[PDB]
Length: 603
Ligand SMILES: C[C@H](N[C@H](C(=O)O)[C@@H]1CCCN1C(=O)c1ccc(C(=O)O)cc1)C(=O)N1CCC[C@H]1C(=O)O
Ligand SMILES: *[C@@H]1O[C@H](CO[C@@H]2O[C@@H](C)[C@@H](O)[C@@H](O)[C@@H]2O)[C@@H](O)[C@H](O)[C@H]1NC(C)=O
Ligand SMILES: *[C@@H]1O[C@H](CO)[C@@H](O)[C@H](O)[C@H]1NC(C)=O
Ligand SMILES: *[C@@H]1O[C@H](CO)[C@@H](O)[C@H](O)[C@H]1NC(C)=O
Ligand SMILES: [Cl-]
Ligand SMILES: [Zn+2]
Image (cartoon, rainbow, N blue to C red):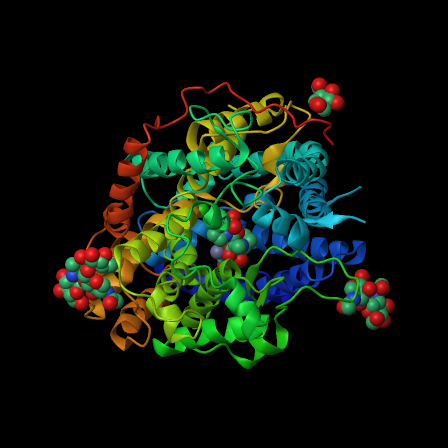
């Protein structure tokens, strides 16, 4: 580690800790910059060489964390809990948690290489018998094929190709991660991840929110199951069991918008999926991003800077190079460079993802003046909610009409139910998977889920929460969790469950602040400068204040609350109950052990 990046002398009291924190944050910018730069170079161009480079940057980061976290331990380990400035307490708390820097060199190197190699296996896996990659080929199959056998072939081929080889690596990663966080005083990695919410009743509150949301999911599930039954027959669909996991329009069954054209109740009304309009008008990736940007600027938030347009990767490179195609947002920590890396396809749900990633960028633009350690969302759920809120407005039929993507819709109940149902497929169907992924990973970190039970515990939670089953037999050689991006990429997941609830609370508050007075699901905050000022206050805070206070200021309440969500979907919730009652559906899947048979002559 460059001497210039090592800590100097500081007094062992609050005033010395303020100086300590300023010199920490100053040198941390350069180290963060070189790390994110090496990751960028790798993720947009996966090679052994770029992997070695990102591992070197990781090692430097770890030496930095060690030098500074040990100094904080030496100076402030006694007293930092007594510091009367709450923000300093937080900055210093964070510095004295060293994470992987608690590891010796040889372990550091093995942790870093584990992360590289897991990343490479996920993003370079392919399904053969020419070869299909996850994005766009398998994604497009899952989304649009209505052939049971072709859907099974992609689902099984992806899970085998990604999950199987990941499993030995994931086990080693888990043990090293846990050894690292345990020396900071956490029971395991999961406990460190949960600490970000600064909330003694975190797990209980989540459980409580889930209980309010579950009836909405169960009604949605049974209505969808009924449509799949008409489309695949009694042999492949059990009206009282879990739904086969490959039939819901997405590799993970994590949101169901892609099968809207199979379940829309009034398919003679104007199609609320504008994909084919975007293709007929000639939309490209760049127009997607420019349309998202203009929404943000209509709110008087910032435009994307030049460095964003010059640096971002907005489409999959044609030049025979391996990339991480999963969409992501990037802050280089230099207050200048911010980019998105997305293999953008022209579809309406991609337009959604574009707003999602740009919400991350906007956050970065809004807090780039803060000292580095405050450059985070108020909690990780806030960072995930920002672009989702704008996408709630963008998706509304009125707004799509404003942007030339739909010829105005008559404002009838049929149009309303069509729209709310499509929104339910996107948001409500996600809720169980958002909740369950970290329940799985917290169990693995805690040791409750050893490697000999990774797949058993995974499908337990998949069936418990989503009510799906694997369409082929799985065993413990399979590692189905590892075929989901965020697992080999070690990105925590509970943020997304938090987000999908928080976004409705934000939306409600923003619509009120824009003076809108219609049904909440028909609000569009476009061009509202007062909504934009209330949003801006959140983004500019970063993590400088507890999320519970930030939320109080914004929404009038200091806790997550499912009510705004329930209010947004109220009409479809009622309609769905009525449909299911009329059809005599059983809610849930009392036939928990059922699996579909294989198709004849598979494969
Ligand atoms: C496509 C969307 N992609 C993710 C994302 O944006 O979240 C990507 C990959 C995981 C993290 N991520 C970031 O881009 C990101 C970058 C930085 C930070 C930070 O500064 O802390 C946070 C996130 C997503 O997975 N999603 C969207 C909602 C559901 C979830 C999924 O598809 O499984
Ligand atoms: C749409 O109409 C609303 C009043 O009508 C109610 O909702 C519509 C969708 C019909 O289903 C009708 O039977 C309902 O009673 C107004 O509140 C609303 O502001 C209108 N929205 C817009 C944007 O025009
Ligand atoms: C990808 O990085 C490697 C270095 O390993 C090299 O082939 C080349 O510089 C890069 N390709 C592009 C297009 O940047
Ligand atoms: C798991 O399933 C595959 C394919 O059905 C099979 O080849 C393999 O034997 C299994 N692993 C174990 C331990 O059975
Ligand atoms: Cl999180
Ligand atoms: Zn995100």
